[PDB]
Image (cartoon, helix red, strand yellow):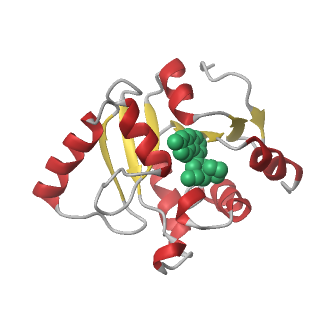
């Protein structure tokens, strides 16, 4: 039993809710919140900008030190950093950004990072300003992630389309 509330169950291990991931993280304090990161960990907008703003820019400060030491992530890759006031840990995952021309096949690799964590609160990778079809992202999630994932979808209209079209 865990503390996630109000989710619709899609499969054995995937759950979904119309929610603001920032507010959801603030209330649940999950072990892992996933950020929709880019390779430079520049958290300017979308989910990343919202999560970073909620940390009062501490996420960005930590991220800048990470990049200065380690260099950029790979598209499809991830790193574990602090969850600050939102979670124990933040798993920064880089899905492909269609608006930069990156290969959508890398979306499966991106979701594979979730399998290293037993339970996660996450957004749909490559959705929103990353330009992929969220219906496709949900399908890849369900077909790739085997650990327990709680998906937060900010847009109510999109949430209803994802549920109604789910096979
Ligand atoms: O940029 C659009 C991208 C963002 N995503 C999110 N998902 C879950 N929680 C979210 N909280 C936020 C707070 C923000 F200020 C900005 C974005 C989010 C967000 C999923 C979607 C939005 C509909 C599909 O796309």
80 to the left or right of 167: left
Name the residue at 59% across, 57% down: 128
Out of 128 and 87, give the one closest to the viewer. Answer: 128
Q: Is residue 56 visible?
A: yes
Name the residue at 83% across, 52% down: 161
State the image coordinates of residue 21 (x, y, percent, origin top left).
55, 35
State the image coordinates of residue 131 (x, y, percent, origin top left).
58, 67
The part of the image, by quadrant, that contains residue 16 is: top right
Query: Which image quarter holds the N terminus?
Result: top right
Q: Is residue 124 visible?
A: no
The part of the image, by quadrant, that contains residue 15 is: top right
Out of 80 and 71, give the one closest to the viewer. Answer: 71
The residue at the far left in this view is: 69
20 to the left or right of 82: right
Name the residue at 43% across, 28% down: 31
Q: How many marks?
A: 0
State the image coordinates of residue 154 (x, y, percent, origin top left).
65, 41
Query: Which image quarter holds the C terminus?
Result: bottom right
């Amino acid at each position: 039993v865990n503390s996630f509330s109000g989710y619709l169950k899609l499969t054995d291990n995937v759950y979904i809710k119309n929610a603001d991931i920032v507010e959801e993280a603030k209330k649940v304090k999950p072990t892992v919140v996933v950020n929709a990161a880019n390779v430079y960990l520049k958290h300017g907008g979308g989910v990343a900008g919202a999560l970073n703003k909620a940390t009062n820019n501490a996420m960005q400060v930590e991220s800048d030190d990470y990049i200065a030491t380690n260099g950029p992530l790979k598209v499809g890759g991830s790193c574990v950093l602090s969850g600050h006031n939102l979670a124990k840990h933040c798993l920064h995952v880089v899905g492909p950004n269609v608006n930069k021309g990156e290969d959508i096949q890398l979306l499966k690799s991106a979701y594979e990072n979730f399998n290293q964590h037993e339970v996660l609160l996450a957004p749909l990778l490559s959705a929103g300003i990353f330009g992929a079809d969220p219906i496709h992202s949900l399908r890849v999630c369900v077909d790739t992630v085997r650990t327990n994932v709680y998906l937060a979808v900010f847009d109510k209209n999109l949430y209803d389309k994802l549920v109604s079209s789910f096979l």
